[PDB]
Amino acid sequence: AECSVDIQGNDQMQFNTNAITVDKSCKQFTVNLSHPGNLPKNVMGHSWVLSTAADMQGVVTDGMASGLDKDYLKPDDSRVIAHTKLIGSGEKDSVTFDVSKLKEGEQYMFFCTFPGHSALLKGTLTLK
Ligand SMILES: [Cu+2]
C-alpha cells in the first residue's frame, strides 16, 4: 500500500504494527483503522491518534479527562496532527492527512487515547 496503511487494534490490547513509514513523496497519508474483537468501545475502545512524541503524554492525559463523550480526545487539540474517531469491535474508521504536516527528523507517535491504553497501543510514525 503506497501512501496508506491498514491497522488493527484488538481485544488483546495489540496494534498489528508498532512502526509506520510515511514515504516523503506522499502528498496525503491515509490510515485505515479496524477493530476485531467482542468488546464494546466503552470498555475496550480504540482510536489512532497522531502527535509528536513530545506531546503524547498531555494529549493522552487530556484525552482521558475528556470522557467517552469526546472519544477521549480533547476537542480541537492543536497538539494532534491527525486522529481517527474512537471505535469498538466490528467498527472501522479511516483518517487522511497532509504529509506536509510532518517535519523530517522530528519524531511522532501514534496511540489510542482510551484510559490507560497508550502504553500498549502505540508505535512510531516516520517521514522517509
Ligand atoms: Cu484503545
Image (cartoon, rainbow, N blue to C red):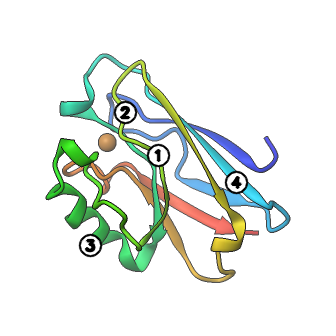
Residue at position x 27%, y 63% in the image:
60
Q: Amino acid at mark 2?
A: Ile
What secondary structure is found at the residue carrying circle 4?
strand
Question: In the rendered structure, which disc, 2 or 3, sits on the residue that comes first in sequence?
Answer: 3
- What is the x, y in percent for residue 24? 80, 68
Q: Residue at x 16, y 48 (%)?
A: 67
Residue at mark 3:
58
Asked if disc 1 and disc 3 are in contact, CB closer than 8 Å, the reply is no
Check disc 1 and report the residue beneath it: 84
Q: Residues within 10 Å of mark 4 (few under 14, many from 20)?
A: some
Q: Please state the total of marks drawn on the protein image.
A: 4
Q: Disc 4 marks which amino acid? A: Phe
Quarter of the image that includes the C terminus: bottom right
Residue extending furthest toward the bottom: 105
Q: Is residue 39 left or right of residue 93?
A: left
Element assignment for label 2: loop
The residue where tag 2 is placed is 87
Mark 3 CB within 8 Å of ligand 1: no
**Image location of residue 32, percent across then percent down:** 59, 38
Lower sequence index among marks 1 and 3: 3
Q: Which mark is residue 23?
A: none
Label 3: how many residues lie within 10 Å, few (<14), some (14-19) or many (20+)? few
* Image side of residue 42 versus residue 109, left or right: left
Residue at image mark 4 = 29
Specify the farthest residue to the front.
Answer: 76
Between the residue at mark 1 and the residue at mark 2, the CA separation in whole angstroms equals 9 Å
